[PDB]
Length: 293
Ligand SMILES: CN(C)c1ccc2c(-c3cc(C(=O)NCCOCCOCCCCCCCl)ccc3C(=O)O)c3ccc(=[N+](C)C)cc-3oc2c1
Ligand SMILES: [Cl-]
Image 1 (cartoon, rainbow, N blue to C red):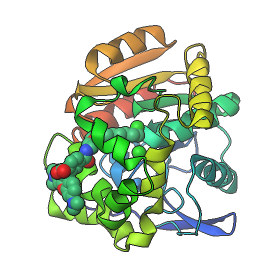
Image 2: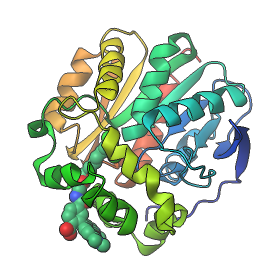
Image 3: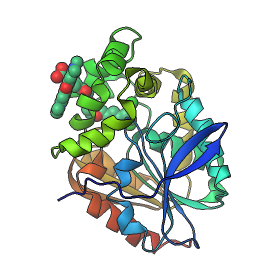
Image 4: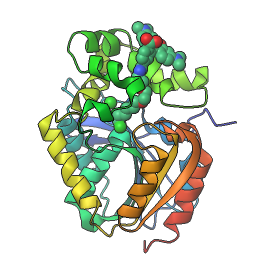
């Protein structure tokens, strides 16, 4: 079955006075592949995809500040905080040019870095990614009341911080196949203490929905503007029925974005890595071999 373990040797690097954990495997020469997780996951989400890429390319998978095995400073965990820590992480590792593999909130981080540093990005593989949601009618109806609730300091904090709903409920609702107890426990591990759940609550409060927050909407519009014009090689994974990227939309996006190939993963919602890791990892490895890296 789909693997549940996390065998990777831990690595830590000091970034802005705090430690960030990261997976680092594969050959030391060549162009590295940087994997960026989102909410409420960690590098664990890449555990079954990296084994297809690591034979031929270095794979680096950080845990975002406040998540995974990374330290937990008392921040707001705004998107800007993740930007500062990820920018510093990339420079601390001395990375020059990279290929990005990104998902969901990791996709906003990755696209925003790539737009600012296009000479250092040799390709982007992405899935169930963040674009502006113009009105609440474009948010998936089955998750609309909950995300509206999450975006409050009363009910949203009760749900996400006190009751851990993002881990116990939203995470499984983003995977078609059933998650095992061992997998759930890996996802729960960084957040056993409620107070550490701050990033899980700030993230949905940052989503660019109905114009709000305006600073995030502007930033995401900007990287989308770039992505529709840039010749950067693109690999878009999508699933059925999907969540943010449904099949008919994925096909339209791939034909509109330059130098984009789209790959059907089969059944999927948001966390496509949990529904078909072997296809995602084997397609990434094949696509890397086509790049000038
Ligand atoms: C302990 N306690 C107080 C709760 C409360 C609620 C649940 C829910 C649940 C959750 C939602 C819920 O999250 N909607 C949102 C779904 O969004 C999925 C789509 O992806 C969004 C991606 C966004 C991407 C952004 C970056 Cl691109 C709604 C209502 C309830 C409910 O049952 O009231 C559970 C639901 C499932 C579940 N299992 C399958 C084991 C367990 C649950 O255990 C709860 C415990
Ligand atoms: Cl979120």
